[PDB]
Length: 199
Image (tube, rainbow, N blue to C red):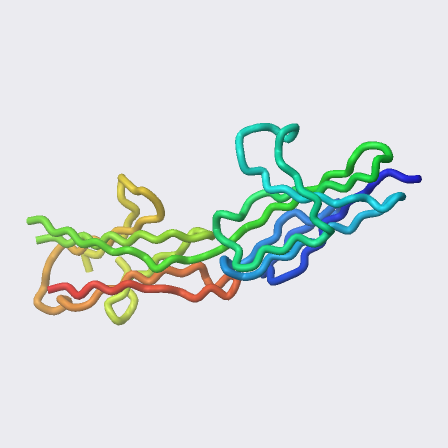
C-alpha cells in the first residue's frame, strides 16, 4: 500500500501555461475555448480523483468536491469559470493529496463609446471589459497623440476607461474618431474598435 499523490497536467486549448519546479501554476485559455486538466495520480490502491471550484465563502472543510475520473473538461469556457481548481486524490492510505491550478480566462469585449460636449470642447469616453487589461488606441483614420489632444483616464470610472478630449474645433478635423482596444493579440484575441462620427 502507498499514499496517494496528485499531479495536474494541462491539456486542451490553453494558450499559455506557467509552471515551476513543484507543479503547474497557471492555465491561460481564451473565453469560449475548451479547458482540459489532467490529474495524474500514484499510490496503491489506485486513488480516487476529485475536482472542485472554490466558489463560495465557506472554507475548504465545506466545499463540494465530486468524483470526476481524472480529466476535467469545460467546453466553451466562460470568463466567470476562471479561478482556482483543486484536484484531490485519495485511496484511504495516509492523508489525501490535494493540488490546485489557477485558470485565467482571457477575452476582449467590443468597447462602448459615449460623447459629451460643453462650451467648444468634446469628450469621447471609451470603456471596455477585458482580461488582460487592454490598450486604448485613438484614431482619426490615422493614429493620434499629443494638437491640443488630451488622452487620459478620467476621475470616475466603472472599469477600463479612456477619454479623448478635443479642445478646439477647427473646420478640418470634424469627422470620424475611433477607439480601438487591444490586448496585443494574446491568446489570438484580435482587436476591436468603435467609431464616432463627429458633426
